[PDB]
Image (cartoon, rainbow, N blue to C red; front, top):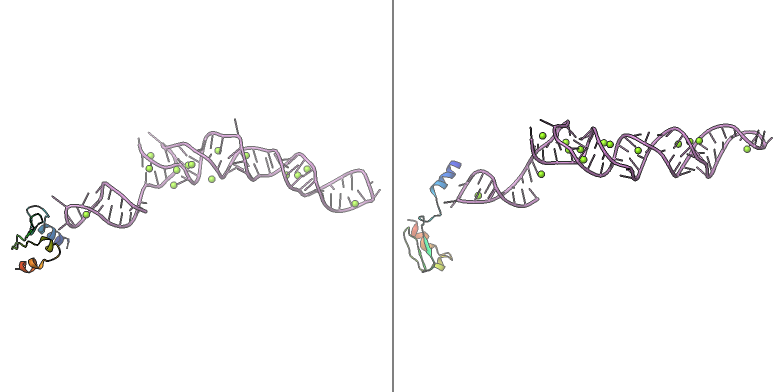
Length: 60
RNA sequence: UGCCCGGUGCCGGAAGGUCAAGGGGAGGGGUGCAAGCCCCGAACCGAAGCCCCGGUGAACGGCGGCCGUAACUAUAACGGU
Ligand SMILES: [Mg+2]
Ligand SMILES: [Mg+2]
Ligand SMILES: [Mg+2]
Ligand SMILES: [Mg+2]
Ligand SMILES: [Mg+2]
Ligand SMILES: [Mg+2]
Ligand SMILES: [Mg+2]
Ligand SMILES: [Mg+2]
Ligand SMILES: [Mg+2]
Ligand SMILES: [Mg+2]
Ligand SMILES: [Mg+2]
Ligand SMILES: [Mg+2]
Ligand SMILES: [Mg+2]
Ligand SMILES: [Mg+2]
């Protein structure tokens, strides 16, 4: 199991720069989910919990 | 060749506590007609030792536990007790 634990550690990573899946930029009001990728302009509405816009569209 | 002198040992301490023989003799008793003779006996004075106050490890000896915490884990330099 600890070998499987390190498999998680070694396959996640790394809360670092070149490592985004979505980019919430509050200085020009956008949240690009650079995976798919939607471009909703309601930044302070996504921070309130409107992730359906992303979840359902990113289950593909 | 580190840290611990609380326990034991040794060393130092004319204070204080306790301390035997002895000294002392408030008081009490036996007996005698009696002077007397004989026996207990409090306060108080009275050594070392012990207590007490310190020192001492190349003196006898002794030198912990639990809990949490860091770039996603592990570990814990750090903290709490
Ligand atoms: Mg110390
Ligand atoms: Mg000692
Ligand atoms: Mg000693
Ligand atoms: Mg001592
Ligand atoms: Mg002595
Ligand atoms: Mg006497
Ligand atoms: Mg006498
Ligand atoms: Mg008489
Ligand atoms: Mg006497
Ligand atoms: Mg003495
Ligand atoms: Mg002793
Ligand atoms: Mg030594
Ligand atoms: Mg000891
Ligand atoms: Mg940690």
